[PDB]
Length: 434
Image 1 (tube, rainbow, N blue to C red):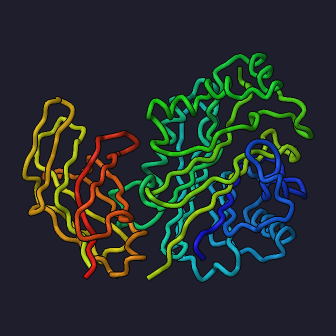
Image 2 (tube, helix red, strand yellow):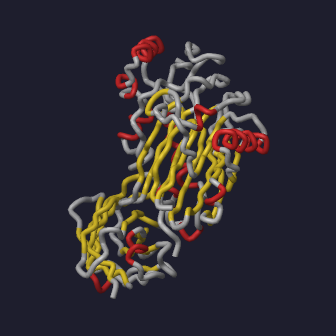
Image 3 (tube, rainbow, N blue to C red):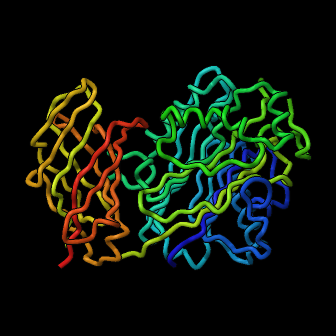
């Protein structure tokens, strides 16, 4: 297959079991950007379900999902992984025909505790490869409370740093760069900064823009504190918290201000195919004080199966240090990782920054495992900038897609470390074939 259809769902189940029928959740029918126009269901290739306050036992729950999907699609979807941590649970299921294509499956979980609050907060994860394309899925439940934004941001950073999904050799990189596509979703619990009656007025009008301008997740993302260079599809569904059970007619009630607690975000390597086909919530599933949120994505995949030469590399790096620096290059297209020599020039007209330059002589050629053009296009390099005394100052990713040829092509990208922008990097390179 050339592309796959990925379903992501997030639902705080409110410590009661689901209703018998959750079909709207699976088929992206409800409010927001929806697939209500689709009369005959196209079964997705991969279903991913993240839940919180899921008080159904692991085994029984996975069975309910397999059962639900069986009745909808007339297919025995196979669960490749599942992972729970208290009542935070994720499960990933694939079509039977894709079972051979999956490999390198891992799971992880992380606790993020804070004193004097209701704990049981943290995250669970699943990653795998679909042929040559790596996928990461994170399901979390962060700290609740209107005034706990700083605590939520810290939960995010603790997850980003501690969650050990994927290959170990990528331990200079965190989960924001380990996977071709990363989906981070769950009960993020960021809230609306507005009085209760004024918010209910806007929900009645279906005027979401004035509420989105006071959404705490949106504001923190603009400050560059969480979810650096992630995407979220535009929100056009009402707040998913907090409803009275048995209906969606009525919000319950600053401790119960309506909010978009339940969210899906993604982070992709550059020059890859990824389109969001839905992002919304149901309005006919009423067992929880939250509503289920869905998202679907069309995602490109690459089959499973010559040298790379750099003219020069130049990095603006954020630091007070003045030592020498080098680069390590990692990729799944390489047999072993390579390293550069010392940088051979450096300058600065800023106390906080440093320009660091590697000439062609200081940079090694990389030798890929296959010489096929169609293979090489779909690959990426992971670069980490390290100092000579030795910890990383910055990581980034570079696509080879437009770099295939005889003459060297320009690249420019951002450097990050531990959820902070730490500079940029640029250079000139070619992937040559004989």
